[PDB]
Length: 493
Ligand SMILES: CC(=O)N[C@H]1[C@H]([C@H](O)[C@H](O)CO)OC(C(=O)O)=C[C@@H]1O
Image (cartoon, rainbow, N blue to C red; front, side, top):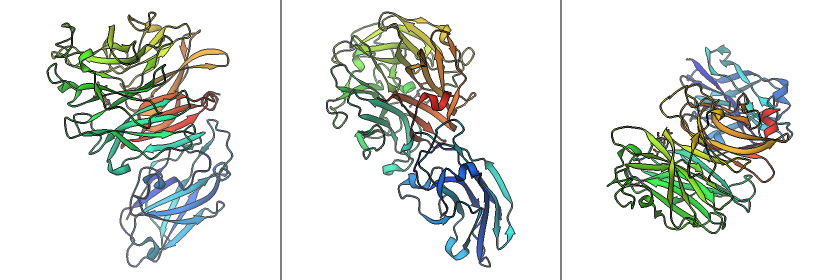
């Protein structure tokens, strides 16, 4: 006869409805001799001012996210509470044998969006006919306000059990393209059966089209995923992705293949996928020095189109069956994706790597630290010839990498050229999604700022037209893909 309690720590945005603050779970249904349950809670005046209404929600599901994020797959009743009240009661009959209770709120309109712009509440008492039950707290509540915050892909959406691997792209016309692994049966990588799914926004991420499967996987060893995105200088959209067996199961004669698809109408329609594995490695490769290589995949998220028009993604390539490590090469095209070539080797024992354009026209590459090498720090390299040749740049190091994909944006802050990098803070785990700012002139990283506390993994970022940052992250143990919008001052002033 015990209650367990979880405070909620997901972000919120103005005017959102029925946002959970804390939820509690009874160990058992109320007994037949129970007439009413009554829950007492604490809620600071600072939180009270930022909400317009409270509610007690009752459900037969114990959910991770806000109940409306499940688009009806969670069933609940909702009972309002005056914001000034600190207790509420409900009849056993109305609970109808259910065990999961949520204290939720409607978020007001005003906001300052600073680091201290947070919301919290705590359940202090759950009494059944005046008998307090033992209460155990597993997590506190702290919900930060952002300019935008929306779960774009939630486990269960459209009948897929899971979602992973976010990719985000803003077009020259302002269209937002969001893509992801639709991980149908569970959260594991290829060779599992996986689709590529998409949603679009034409209003800067205020609203999003219904999700559309654009590449359908056809069974185990026949799925697709790990999408990266660019817009070419001629204006076409380009996705690149892998499909087939797993990374370490690929071979020269039976590869996990690399594909590209293009769109000429802002992501509405896409060309039938085109196998470009033969430009890279394996049995159909024209370069005999790469015909015995085993595997290649481009880092999911975004590529980079250079000022010349050269299209680039970083591939991480397995050259030997005698080792489980990868080497980085830039995959590029100077003819709008018609043909593809590889740079010289950019990193030895690398992994998922990302590119960004330096103020002086050099290319900066950020390299995932796979295998807890060295000091468990993120790796960096530099190229001065548009990605053809590379050199390690230790002076950019200085942030921890638990072994996870992330992203870079070149931005101006207070007149000064800086790199914004997204990565889990950890330590040594995929936890607390954070961003850092690297100052070009001083060569020092900022202290991290945690955007989403809790389990956090892959992230992609884009610069919106008005300077806001779109931040697309893997939140939680069973992952939802979440689009968050903030400006730099919200995080760093
Ligand atoms: C094609 C592929 O396998 N991509 C996977 C990537 C890769 O396995 C690793 O980067 C190599 O070390 O890892 C992860 C991961 O969450 O860690 C997710 C990707 O789906």
